[PDB]
Image 1 (cartoon, each protein chain N blue to C red):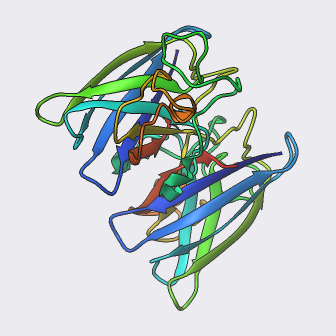
Image 2 (image 1 turned 60 degrees about the horizontal axis):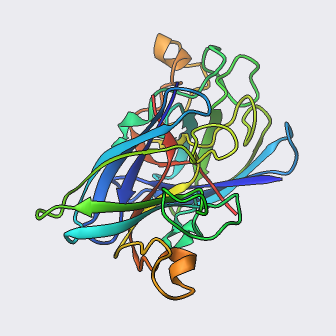
Length: 153
Length: 153
């Protein structure tokens, strides 16, 4: 019955709080929060490898992928453990997040504690942008805000 | 051969970067970094329970103590897993940290990843302070800066 949390922060107006809960071992992780300061639309929403924030979101590393799969979307079999796809900002720059992934984990093989959550500038083509990059980051662009995923009460 | 890192930040001028390395499982954790913005002198230096930073350093919780023991110094048998004692700011407000604890861990029973590192306003009486509070928090005072301990490369 583990829970985690993450405070997203960046140079920009982008900022938010995201919550993680995984009622059962191995079970799904419910992900929910709110983010403001985003352009209206879709933004790449990924768990990168390191909880390193010494050089800002830059130092977070690549998508978190214990598995050396290519990029992809949440529902894709070939995907990074950390591709949570995209989040949607309404007309008031507010993305209201409610996700439920079964690849990520708050414990065990794909534990994401101590790692960084990043919301990207533009959307994640899920690997359908027709160029090498689309198969790497799904062409997400600059990292607007991040935060180390820490253990909540 | 696991490594971790933490970026300390607070409302004040206090800020810094702290590094964790634990070459062997169960082995000691080498702790080192620099902190600036501190009054010259000694400051309480503790790992608190939660990587929750939603309400700033406030939301970090109590000293991290899986043990349910009494507060104390790093060199005590009776101490919290997270009492790293104190750090020392020179005449230029710079504390240069080099510690080596064997109670904390980057893996296993006393894992501290996903948790918050806090440097306090005043010093940690080490329990030798004369009042119950001394033996709850070594009377450290307001929390000047913190950061969730994340996984480094």
